[PDB]
Structures are given as structure tokens and as C-alpha cells.
Image (cartoon, rainbow over all chains, first blue to last red; front, side):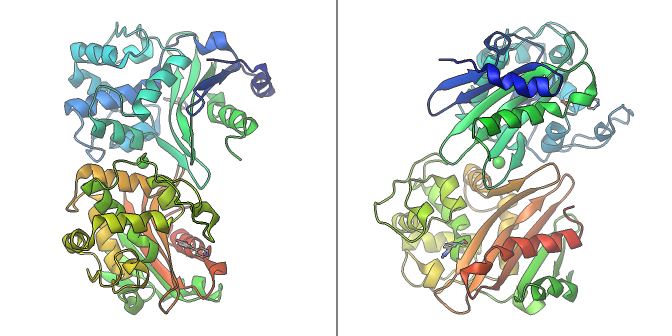
Length: 242
Length: 242
Ligand SMILES: O=C(O)c1cccc(-c2ccncc2)c1
Ligand SMILES: O=C(O)c1cccc(-c2ccncc2)c1
Ligand SMILES: [Cl-]
């Protein structure tokens, strides 16, 4: 079941923003959120779509392994980190859109659609440009649906090879220490309203795993750092991390 | 290719200790150490042997995956974390000797011997008790030999399944942030003189990989923390980590 905790809103109001945090206790099979309605509100996935995109590219051979180099095309873009060669790890670390756009082109409209249906991903609607539908197309997904999708990935239950799912889980590595491990992916939807920021993944503990998925209104890029900051303060309140 | 940098000794002396640090730049294929002799002096692997031990156990089916639970045998031991159920992740995280002793028993002398030779691991001598040879048996490995093994693990070139190697590298995960990822294994040898502590692994960067292997005199358990502190103080000096 699910369960609402309005107290987390204090973290959002503390930063003069508003959004939703959704946690899932794998052991107890229980979910927690500050806003059950927005937890089920479907938004554009934006760069969080790089998870299923990576899975499909790997399983089809578009990506050989996490070391394959995808050379810069030479176009100077507003994000400096995008103007250099990348591999799967760095491409996901820096949310390099142009690399995954090339993945989607080679994947193809048809194969992308078939796989997202097998993943049961959001509304499964890729309408728009094959190389930007997750940014300005018709695909939509809610926070609870992210967790459902993420859970399949953790258990290697998605309909792709185990290898592909392990590699993507490796590429999602964000932070790790003696207390926890975080495998997650950021997102920043700016092309179509509402402008929001994503952060979806999970926290690995010794004896349990806490899946999470959060989105928040992001009218300007200054507040991107709040995606992780607000998430972590909820984790510290729930005593999941020191 | 190899170069000696006696300046690093300052990090050992300010802590009233002695030891060796060995670095290998994968891109440039160059190695650096503070003591060429000790870098090639072979010691007992101790708990660093849990890398090859895990690889063999996985490849033979002794360990099904990183989720298989290994039940505490109900015998109280002086290490609190050992009086607990474990999987490969927590077992390696907490150096749970009893769990790996059962691995070796199930693996068997013959298969254990055969595999270590394929790995070209240390002196490849499993002489002693199958359930403790890496602690008070005849097997020996030097810091430089550890790196040659670690490098084969990183490139999946060892004579075991790719999956087995990916799993162990996941279990080796120790620390991660926006600047680097560390996958390593600690060691603490006390049954045969000299008493030492190990730390072998590597640092993953965006554009390079730094392999490392260090051991230091450990007369008492009070200085175990210096294994990581000293190693990191060298990494900062070589500007491998901020
Ligand atoms: O957080 C993300 O996922 C993401 C993706 C693409 C671009 C940017 C971005 C845009 C402007 N200034 C800073 C960062 C962020
Ligand atoms: O650091 C390790 O890898 C390790 C492995 C096994 C045991 C111990 C140990 C033994 C006594 N007191 C404290 C710790 C340490
Ligand atoms: Cl990993």
C-alpha cells in the first residue's frame, strides 16, 4: 500500500519550492510520499529516460559495452561537458543528450516502441521525434511508475539480458560509502511546461533497498541542486542515512 | 617504466609507520612506488584473497549471485558484524572470513589450485588448510602482483565468466562521488610475521584508471585506518583525487 506524510513538505517550503518525494521500502513492500496525487502525476521523463535508453541500446548492440567511445561531433553546445568524447558511464554521468539521441536514431522508431511496451514504461507513447520524444514528445511517466520500472531493473526482471541490466546499474552509480550506495539518474525538463527536475533511483543498504523517485518545479536552473538536497533530507528524516 | 618516488615515505613516517604504496597509470602504462623492493616482496594475501575466492565461487555455482544469503552458523565470534547473515556484498564489505572459509571448503583444493594458476595469482601455492591457506598457509603475493591481477579483472580478461567478474567488481565497490569511484578490498594479516595490512584496488576516473596496491606494518589493529588514509594522502599528492 501507500501512505502520505505531509511533514516532508517542510523541506520543500524551506527552499521556497514545491514538489514530491516517493520512497518504497522493498523489505516491507510499503510506499511513502508527501503528495499521493503528484506522486501519480505523469510528466515528461527527460534525461531520466537515459536508463531505458541505455538498456535498449546495449541489448540491441548499438552499444558494445561501457568502454565504447562515442566521439564528439564537433558542435559547440551550451554545456561544456557535452563537447568531448564519452562512454556510457560519462554520458550518463553528465546527461549527454546528443550521445543518446544518436542511440535512439540507430535504435529506430519501431524497436523503441516495442521495448518500452515490454518495459511497461509510462504511457508507452513515443510520438514525436525519435531523437527527442523523451524531451518534447508525448511520452509521460509518474514517480510511482518510475519506482515500478526501477524495481524490475534491480531484480534483473526487465525483458533484456542480465548483462545489459548490470551495465546500466553500474552506469547509474552516483554515490557510495560505508553507509549506503546510490544508483540514480537526474532529469531536467525544460522544453514543455511544466518545467521540472527529476531524480530517480534507489538507496542500497546492508539488509534493505529504498527505491525513490522525486520531481520538483524547476522554473530556472539555479535550483537543480535541490533535487538531491531535498531528497537526502527526507532520507535523513526517515533515518535511512545518517 | 617503473619509477621510485621516495617522497611518499613522508606520509608513512608522520604516522610512525612503514609500508609501500604502488600506483599504475593505465593510460600511460607507467607505475610509481615509494619502495621498489617492498613493492615486489610477497606477503600473505589475507582478506584480499576474497577477490579470487569470490570469482571462483561464482564461476562454479558455489555462489549463485550477489543476493544468495549465507546463514550465520550460530557461533559467537569476536567480530560483531560476523555474527550475522550475509550476502556477497556485505560479506566482502565486512571481511566475513567464516563465509569465505565455507566457500573454499566447497570449492575444494583441486579446483582452487587449478583456478589460481589460471589467474597467475601470487605464487599459486595453496599449501596448507583449504579453509585458511590465505591466512596462515603458503600462498604469497606482492603488491605489483596484485595490480597485474586487478588489471585483468578490470578488463574481464581473467579465465572465468564475464558475469562472475562483473559481480565481484560490484562487490568491490567501496566509495563513489562526483570525482572518482573506488573498488578495492582490505586485508589484515596477523597469523604469520610480519603483521601487515593490505589495501588493493583502483580509482576510476572519467578519462583514466589508477590501479593501486599497498601494504604496511600493522603491529596492532589500532592503525588499520591508516591503510586508506595513507593511500589517499598519496593520491592527493599525485593529484589523482582532489
Ligand atoms: O540535471 C540534468 O539532468 C540536466 C540535463 C541537461 C542540462 C542541464 C543543465 C542545464 C543548464 N544549466 C545546468 C545544467 C541539466
Ligand atoms: O581489515 C580487515 O580486512 C580485517 C579482516 C579480518 C579481521 C579483521 C580484524 C581483526 C581483529 N580486530 C579487528 C579487525 C580485519
Ligand atoms: Cl557497480
